[PDB]
Amino acid sequence: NERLRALEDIEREIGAILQNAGTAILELSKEKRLLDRQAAAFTTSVQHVEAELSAQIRYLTQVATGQPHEGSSYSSRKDCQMALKRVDYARLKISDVARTCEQML
Amino acid sequence: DAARIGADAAQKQIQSLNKMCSNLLEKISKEERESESGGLRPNKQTFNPGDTNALVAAVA
């Protein structure tokens, strides 16, 4: 759950770091203010993105041997399907009884 | 014109300022590289079965 958001934020930060490095290079090579701080921030963000990528790659490696988490609660799915079918059949029978009663009265 | 403005602030002074900015940026980049070179290896941590194996239960 949180690892997905972490990887998404890491990718967004890598993109932002690339953009900041490009902008800092442009501002520094245009003419010769904040170019030094911009380059420092860009280098720091690039290093942080690299560290985050290395940490995510150095994960616990849950299985890496076969198809893990086999069985997605299919029994519960089938039970819920049968319950819904029972409810639908009950509704149909109740509607039939109601039509019979309306024809009676 | 080759500078479009000025005489003392012409392409000579512009190139000098650009070289100064480039030297500052190169020094900053070299400092960042020397700081990042300290990373030895991603030393993770896990269980320690080497001790608990001999320390596992037995007839004793």
Image (cartoon, coloured by chain):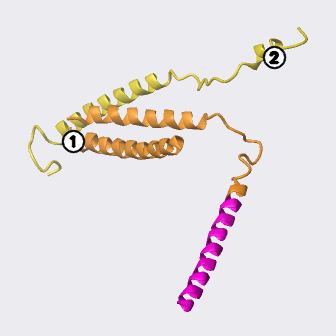
- Palette colour of chain B: yellow
Q: What secondary structure is found at the residue carrying circle 1?
A: loop
Q: Residue furthest left?
A: B6
Residue beneath the point at 48% across and 44% down: A5
**Residue A36 found in image quarter:** top left
Mark 1 Cα shell of 10 Å, populated few (<14), some (14-19), many (≥20): few
| Dot 2: chain letter | B
Q: Which of B43/A17 is in front?
A: B43
Q: Please identify the quarter of the rendering in which residue B21 is found.
A: top left
For residue B19, say whether it is visible.
Answer: no
Q: How many numbered circles are shown?
A: 2
Q: Identify the element where label 2 is drawn.
A: helix
| Of A37 and B48, the residue lying toward us | B48
Residue at image point 29% right, 45% down: A26
Q: Amino acid at mark 2?
A: Asn
Placement of B46 over or under B55, stated as above or below: below
Does the stretch in magenta take in A47? no
Closer to us: A52 or B54? B54
The residue under the point 34% across, 43% down is: A20
What segment is highlighted magenta in the picture? A77-105
Q: Which residue is mark 1?
A: A31
Residue A105 in the image: state x and y as whole percent.
Answer: 52, 89
Residue A63: percent from the left, percent from the top? Answer: 72, 40
Q: Which mark is residue B53?
A: 2
* Residue name at image x 47 percent, y 46 percent: A8
Q: Position of residue B13 (x, y in %)?
A: 17, 36
Q: Is residue B47 left or right of residue A95?
A: right
The chain coloured orange is: A
A89 drawn magenta: yes
